[PDB]
Amino acid sequence: HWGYGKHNGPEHWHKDFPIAKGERQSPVDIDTHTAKYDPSLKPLSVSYDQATSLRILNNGHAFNVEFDDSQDKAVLKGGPLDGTYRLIQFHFHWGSLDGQGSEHTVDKKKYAAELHLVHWNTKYGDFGKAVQQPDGLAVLGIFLKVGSAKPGLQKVVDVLDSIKTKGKSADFTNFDPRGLLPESLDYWTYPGSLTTPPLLECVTWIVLKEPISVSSEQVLKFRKLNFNGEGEPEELMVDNWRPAQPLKNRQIKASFK
Ligand SMILES: CCCCCOc1ccc(S(N)(=O)=O)cc1
Ligand code: NA
Ligand code: NA
Ligand SMILES: [Zn+2]
């Protein structure tokens, strides 16, 4: 099965997922000087006040915080999007060291980690149908740098001990994802893909310019998770990021001048 090791990592994925070499793969490097300000881009509308988190799961690749997406509660609208996208889960990618971990890069800069808030287009009815469409998903990406602690992240950090290994989950209700945002909703946007297998080309990427700060202690706890299941040899869950992919025939557009 695919993973992030030398034997099964990003260089191998194309053998079982040939779209890995497709025309709109993610992540990409964001070249800030050539991303063009688009004054027709609308402000992002993030409506998370009614979000219903349910559970946190170590899936062997990251941890996912899952939401009740059986109704229009937490939704993303506006920005580059047409119509309404429902939040289904968030997760992170991070490094073994503070100098790497993000998937997107900014003028080749790697951040310590990257948060992905995953949403699906309600006009397709379910996430499974949305991932059969080129406009099925919208992922809001937020960079993490190491500095002061992020108070809204600490509830996540403090549950990780209970989901150390692949396949473990824990009840995780009443978590407010508004506590993970930065102040500004300035963003870059481009058409891309899932960054893990199956690498499907369904995503409108919306990457916020402003990183959130997290403390060294917070990200260190991410790095104590395990890729392996219980009873198996311990493999620290670190460096679960895909490198930047060729931009090909795409443009990145900035919401801000
Ligand atoms: C039909 C596949 C469902 C399982 C995979 O779902 C994903 C995978 C990657 C991302 S990401 N890193 O691009 O945000 C978001 C959702
Ligand atoms: Na451009
Ligand atoms: Na419901
Ligand atoms: Zn992701």
Image: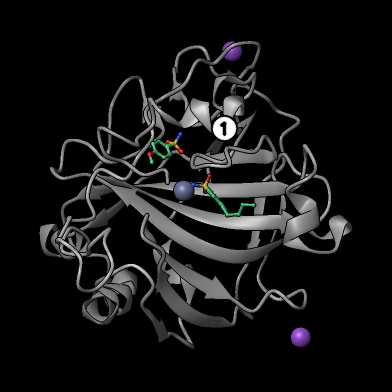
Position of the C terminus by quadrant: top right
Q: Secondary structure at mark 1?
A: loop
Near-viewer residue (213 or 67): 67
Give the residue at x 18% y 58%.
Answer: 223
Q: How is the image coloured?
A: one colour
Q: Is residue 55 left or right of residue 167?
A: right
| x and y, in percent, of residue 2 in the image | 41, 43
Q: Is residue 97 left or right of residue 201?
A: left
Q: Quadrant of ligand 2?
A: top right
Confirm whether residue 198 shows in the render. Answer: yes
| x and y, in percent, of residue 208 in the image | 48, 43
Q: Amino acid at mark 1?
A: Phe
| x and y, in percent, of residue 248 in the image | 59, 11
Near-viewer residue (162 or 80): 162
Confirm whether residue 85 shows in the render. Answer: no
Give the residue at x 70% y 28%.
Answer: 39
Give the residue at x 27% y 58%.
Answer: 227
Q: Is residue 130 left or right of residue 186?
A: right
Position above or below: 182 against 189: below
Say which residue label 1 marks: 17
How many tags in the picture?
1
At label 1, counting other C-alpha atoms closer than 10 Å, the crowd grade (few under 14, some 14-19, many 20 or more) is: some
Give the residue at x 51% y 26%.
Answer: 14
Image quadrant assignment for residue 209:
top left
| x and y, in percent, of residue 131 in the image | 73, 48
Near-viewer residue (189 or 127): 127
